[PDB]
Length: 52
Image 1 (cartoon, rainbow, N blue to C red):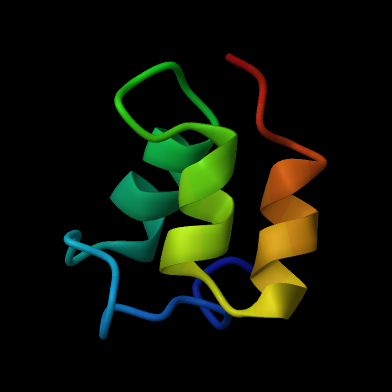
Image 2 (image 1 turned 180 degrees about the horizontal axis):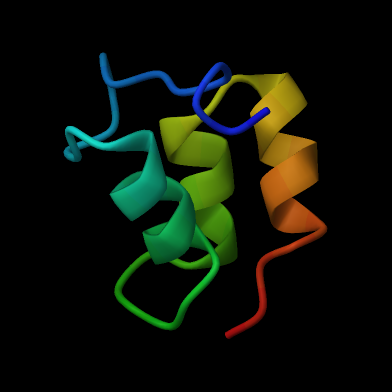
């Protein structure tokens, strides 16, 4: 679940919500943020949910 998979050690975000939602919206970092803000478990779950 996308609170759990959050890796703030490398995500410039303090909220797993704001993080996931960045990764699933057009910004500077949509789909790729799934990789650079979540563990591999959250990555695939985000990269399958991430539509810019």
